[PDB]
Image 1 (cartoon, rainbow, N blue to C red):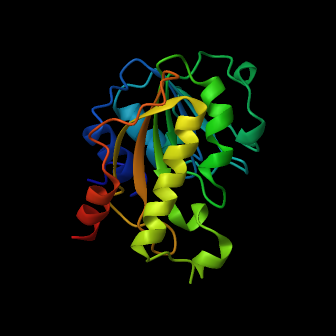
Image 2: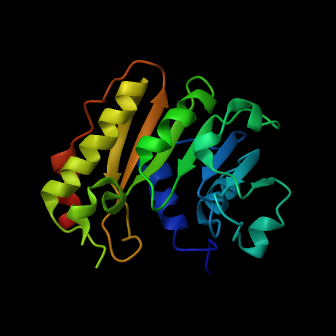
Length: 208
């Protein structure tokens, strides 16, 4: 009864549930596929196709690598990604779980690539969004730094034209032991942060 190929799958599972996302029949993009937990979640929820992208060599679990619905794009730096790179359908849903890089560098090319009214479920990792001097053991524990990193990503998304439809906390810690957050974006050019988005409330709920 391990339902997913990694505990990472628990992260996207919560996003799908909390953000009321529908994957069935959609062409999906998994940025930072790694072992494939996110891809696995999307496959199980009926994705028509999943592009599995990694800046380095693919590390997909055997089960996921062998899946006919999966299109591997390894040694592929998403910063250099353009719409022409996606030749088997335009992604309308995207999940993002990258490390050692800010979403500031991922969201812009993605905004162009994603289908109109396409959606994004993205992990916000304070340890990669804060300043070097702010990090230190590699864990960010300061609530004010957490807030600032969330604010930073929401600002970047809205400046691009994404609307922010939801925000919550990732159900499990990432990497060296970091609280991380899940944000729901919509490509509509409206730059609207939904009323339900409440950073302080999310921070408080994660802490409990």
